[PDB]
Length: 164
Image (tube, rainbow, N blue to C red; front, top):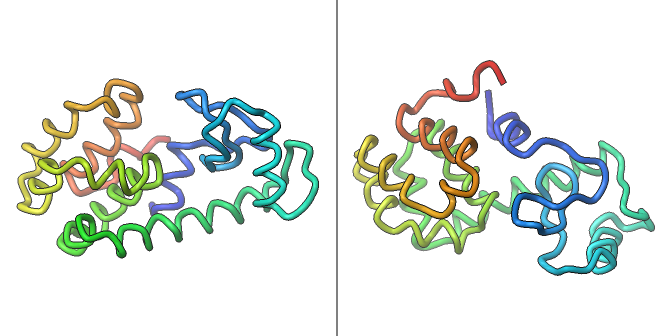
């Protein structure tokens, strides 16, 4: 199992513009188009990202292309982040995958704000962090996903994703 498979599970794959749980427009494999109300705005951003006139629809290859660029940017974001870097460098390979997942979903900025949970992960206090992490809007809005990542940090294995 790896980060691409993991996120492919959590995000799904939609070939047409769609709204995610917070009503924002996306496409592909959890690719944020725009934060605004305009489908037009969204269609606009989509064409600029793809480089062609899409008319709100893209191919699988196109989606995978944005996906690879997005995974790439999440990792780089973590590495350039003063609050995130040390945490990530202190973790094992599986746990690193869980942090990249969070970053991909809510942004560096949103993750760097889980201050207390970050300290706990850094100290290898697995069960304590998992409870802290669950005290969040993030867990209350998308509990099944949040749970999967959380057990992941807890246990350091892919158990939560096997059978998916």
